[PDB]
Image 1 (cartoon, rainbow, N blue to C red):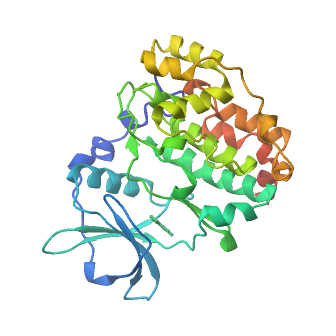
Image 2 (cartoon, rainbow, N blue to C red; image 1 turned 135 degrees about the horizontal axis):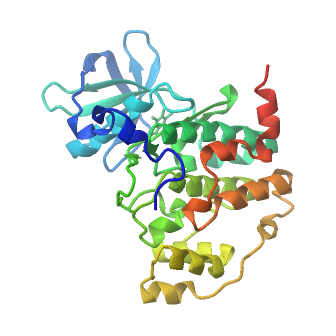
Amino acid sequence: SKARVYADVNVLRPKEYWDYEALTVQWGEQDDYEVVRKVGRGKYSEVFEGINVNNNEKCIIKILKPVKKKKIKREIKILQNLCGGPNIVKLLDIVRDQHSKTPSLIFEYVNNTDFKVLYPTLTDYDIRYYIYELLKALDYCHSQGIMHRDVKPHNVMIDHELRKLRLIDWGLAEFYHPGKEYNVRVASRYFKGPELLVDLQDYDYSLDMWSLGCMFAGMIFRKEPFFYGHDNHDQLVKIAKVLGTDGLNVYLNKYRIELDPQLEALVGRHSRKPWLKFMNADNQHLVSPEAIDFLDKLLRYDHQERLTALEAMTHPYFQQVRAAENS
Ligand SMILES: Brc1c(Br)c(Br)c2[nH]cnc2c1Br
C-alpha cells in the first residue's frame, strides 16, 4: 500500500527536511516566558497558559517531561516544517532550563472553548465553515509529507468569536515514506481507523481522513463519540455494526489480513446501517443529503477509497463556504 497523493514528497526534499534525528536547535531565551496557570496535563507534557514578559502577550507553554530525545526532535522538526501553514498552530519559540535542560515549546495563544460546551451551540453553517478550515490544515500537512495521526475535537482549538481554528498537538505526527511500516499505537481509540485496528502498518495520510470522519459524524448527529468502543477490539465491532461486515471482509481479503480468530468471532456478521437512521428531531437542522454523502465518502474501510483532504474541499457540502471566500 502506498499513498494516492503526496507519496514522494520526502524523496524530493533535502534529507535535512525529514531527518529529524539530525536536528540541532537554536535555543531561545528561557527568561522571556513565564508560566501562569495549568491547562493540564500530560504523560509527557504539561501545558500551561503563559506570558511573554517583553510584550505581555499570552502564550501557551508545553513543558516536555523528560523525554525521549527522538520524539522531542520529531515534534520540533515537524512544527518548524509546518510553521506558517493555514490553520496550523504556530511554534513561536523553543527554550530550555540552562541546567536541567528541560525544554518548553512556546505556542501562539488561542482563546479556545472546549468542544463539549462549544459544539452544542454550532449552526449548520458553523460546522461547514470549521470542517473546511480543518481540511485546509490537513491538506497543507499532507502536502508537506506529514501525517497528523491524532485528529480529534480535543486537538482542534477554536476561538469562536474570531472564527479562528488551529490543529494542535503534533506529538504523534510522522513523516510519510512509501512502504514504511508504522506504529499502529496512534490516534485516540474512538478515532482509530480500521487500518490501526487490523494492524495494517503501511498506512498513510488517509488515516487522518477516517479520524476527521468520526469527528464529523459526532458533530452532525450529536452522537459523541460516534464509534464508542470499550477497548480496541470492541472499537472494530462498533464500526462493523454500522458499515456492515461485507465491506470489512472485502477489505481484509484485499490487503491479505486475517483477524485473530477471537476478534473475528467478536465482530460477527452485520448489515450496513443507513446513515439516515442517526438523524432525529434534536439534530435534523445539522443533517442534509450533502452532509451524509460527505460523511459516507470519508468513513470507508479501505483507506485508498477515502476522500483526500483536497478532494474533500471540493464537496458540495462546502459550496456556501467557498462562495463567501470570494472577492
Ligand atoms: Br489554546 C491551546 C493551545 Br494553542 C495548545 Br498548543 C495546547 N496544547 C494543549 N492544550 C492546548 C491549548 Br488549550
